[PDB]
Image (cartoon, rainbow, N blue to C red; front, top):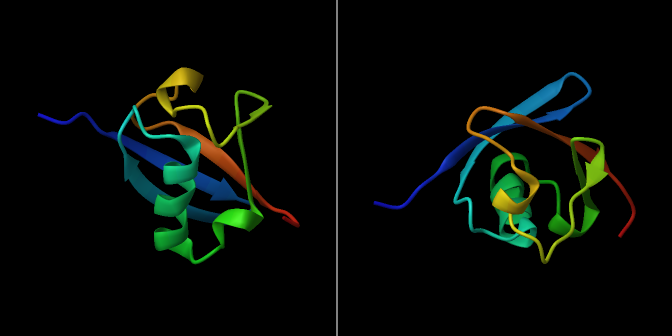
Length: 77
């Protein structure tokens, strides 16, 4: 079976939930976030463990675990 991570996305008072494969790139993670909240991929800055997530790295590479949270900051592309 495919593995999956349930990740909470936080921005101020707002929170959304997505479900993504560990092997997915951050670009595909942002696409899942866009489906959940409508914020364009180009405008998403994601932060986990104090680090901005890079589009060509995987979710797993940042050691994001099932049920953790990632911070979203709307930013200019």
